Amino acid sequence: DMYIERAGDITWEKDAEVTGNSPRLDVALDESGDFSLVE
Amino acid sequence: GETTDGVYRVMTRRLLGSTQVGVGVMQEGVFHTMWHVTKGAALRSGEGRLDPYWGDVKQDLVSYCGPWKLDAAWDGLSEVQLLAVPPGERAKNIQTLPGIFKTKDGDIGAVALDYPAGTSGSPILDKCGRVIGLYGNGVVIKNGSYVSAITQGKRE
Ligand SMILES: Cc1nsc(N[C@H]2CCC[C@]2(C)CO)n1
Image 1 (spheres, protein in one colour):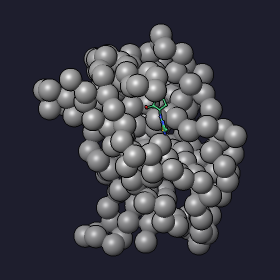
Image 2 (spheres, protein in one colour):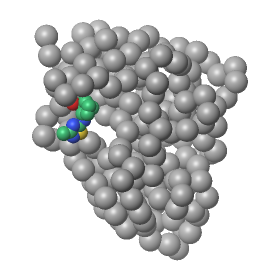
Image 3 (tube, protein in one colour):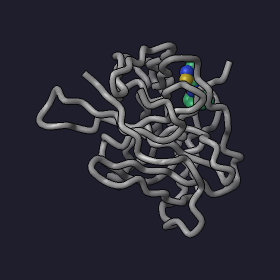
Image 4 (cartoon, chains in turn blue, purple):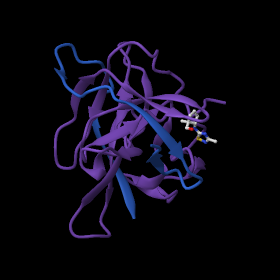
């Protein structure tokens, strides 16, 4: 059985930690909702 | 139960202790999460029941109590924030410039941030605080790190 618990407000935070790159990838989406890389 | 707008953890007592299987967004009386989090099962909020209303395995999305309400989109240029809600950890905003998933049916923004599986359903927001999609369905690249699509539904 599943239950939900509040975890916070949805707001933009000024001075949040900035991380992560921006890759451009060729991908395919199958009927099961799974993404895969095309090369 | 609790219907206040915000980000929520999705928990289960079926496995060892209380385990966080994902995250979701409550907006306008509707709870929004990824399909793989709940598999379309009913949810509890205190003494109240949340019944699925719409879902789609290919989009990997599901809404409870009403139709999908989130319609903001990434503008294709600006930085965004993942409001990551990791298991057992406080909600934390992480700012990133999205990459792109290029498909035969069009392009979609992607966020290159790695978090535990139970973080799926965490919202991605724009500078106005609008939810432009949920985090948690994506791919593992050459290196071994995770890249999630910015998955958004359609507000009918
Ligand atoms: C038929 C379909 N169900 S979900 C979906 N999603 C598309 C819409 C644009 C690109 C996408 C994200 C991946 O091919 N397309």
